[PDB]
Image (cartoon, rainbow, N blue to C red; front, side, top):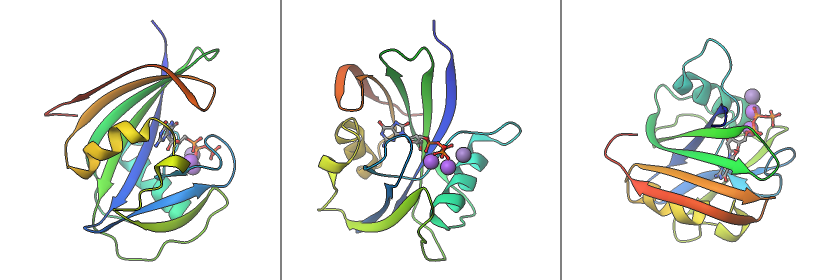
Amino acid sequence: MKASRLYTLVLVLQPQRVLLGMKKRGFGAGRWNGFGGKVQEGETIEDGARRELQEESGLTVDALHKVGQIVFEFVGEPELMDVHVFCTDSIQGTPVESDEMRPCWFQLDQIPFKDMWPDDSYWFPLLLQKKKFHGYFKFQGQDTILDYTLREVDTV
Ligand SMILES: Nc1nc2c([nH]c(=O)n2[C@H]2C[C@H](O)[C@@H](COP(=O)(O)OP(=O)(O)OP(=O)(O)O)O2)c(=O)[nH]1
Ligand SMILES: [Mn+2]
Ligand code: NA
Ligand code: NA
């Protein structure tokens, strides 16, 4: 048994494009990703996701919808990362570069998988199909998956 820490991840997914941010420092630096971070004491997971989206991208949204949950384990780290993944298609301002992220839109036939976390190749297609999922990935360092599970679910 390991303990886990709560994180969020938000994908702004529109009919023909998705907003990603280039992580400028910290965990996952150099990879395009959705927006998110640690859940803080007192806030719901969904509200922490909304907060991180605003902090990192400048976007303010009324609602998010849950699309998946991914648990990450790293060799040498006792704590698991329990990542709650959300989407929305509905925005009403423009993204802005933050200290953490440079936002950029990608067409959905140009998803930059080689410059994303390696596990995203497995679960992001499910997100694109609007299928909910649970995943688990064990990493050695930043690049190498040693074990993983991925399943479609009816409820996140
Ligand atoms: N797509 C994808 N996202 C991941 C993976 N692993 C992982 O932690 N994430 C997400 C979850 C969070 O959105 C983010 C990690 O949180 P963070 O380090 O940005 O947290 P934060 O904003 O609170 O921290 P800080 O950088 O402000 O100090 O990366 C992965 O393998 N794939
Ligand atoms: Mn944070
Ligand atoms: Na953050
Ligand atoms: Na973050």
